[PDB]
Image (tube, rainbow over all chains, first blue to last red; front, side, top):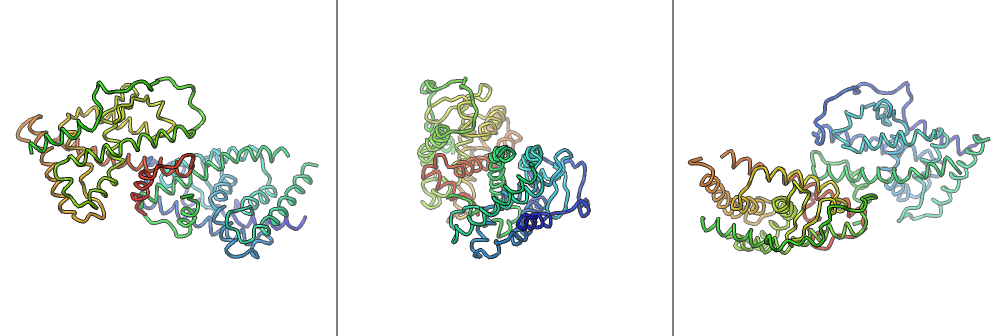
Length: 234
Length: 237
């Protein structure tokens, strides 16, 4: 109802946890961190969260109709160029900033205070954007389309940019249809107005990765490290 | 040695402005008003301030006894590896943090709010460190040795690491004796509070590399090639 939308909705919901399988076994409502620094366990968790998020986004992308038939170089470049944005967007959409809870794609819940040592300030900024995003009340099928459009977009280096644009057209039409059926323009213009906040969060993430890499407590995962190096204009 | 102390003192003094040579013609404590974030003119000033200290610190280093006798590859690595830290320590000591005043090696005086957009938060950390250094009341001969010790120090990739080590021990001996020959015989809490400034300085250097990373990302104005080189040479990945 109709078919593309059902498949985007199903790809989205399968790429994250239900309330049922939310994982509280590391959660603590209060920890007392030494702010402004970090040990190897904090940095390794930060990295494992990034990697595990990319594994899950890759499986989600694989379920967007048309995506797995793009060239493998093209699927790679789309995912790599969109990963930080999608990580931040999906994280903000699923978290609970009214309770200081970051809820990650595996179901793991961690308090803001438990993220502070690995993520630095970035996690605080991500919760602010959670509130910012939640204030728009973006429904699931809308979010399912929008996140996919974050991924399926022009990027410098695509082998088949027109195939990618064609798929962007199909997803945009699918979204317009849904916003019509539901309305029965403005949320989206409202939404587009938060894109500068999102772009700042992406930069804040690259900055956090630079700092950790400088620090070098543990080495970064290969693919995260490629993504970071590839995003650098120099 | 002795004569080391005098040489070190003369190299330091000769590498900065006379009080009578201070330039206040650009100083404004009131800017009109801050937001939004850095534009191109702020960034270009940040790089101009950095670059301005390049030749000065290289000429100062040449006057340290023994520095010109390290290998040329070793002099270049020491200089590049110590550049941000020397810049920061010498700024900190020269400025007047009680008043928000930054005094650069050209003699140029700028208020911290004139600097803030270019430097980011870094300017505030540098200002905290400068308050902290100023409290320790470091005399000029002690400072003359400390700055030299920032420069002449073990670095990855030295060809003659034991020779860097000899010249550094020479300088640390000079310092230690001077701090004993002023502040009580025959012993050195003063001394390890002084030397305690070296790790905090490293930590601030890292904050500089962060700002530069961020500006290169933004890319409104590119670093000049020498700063860029120091940034890329000093990123250990």
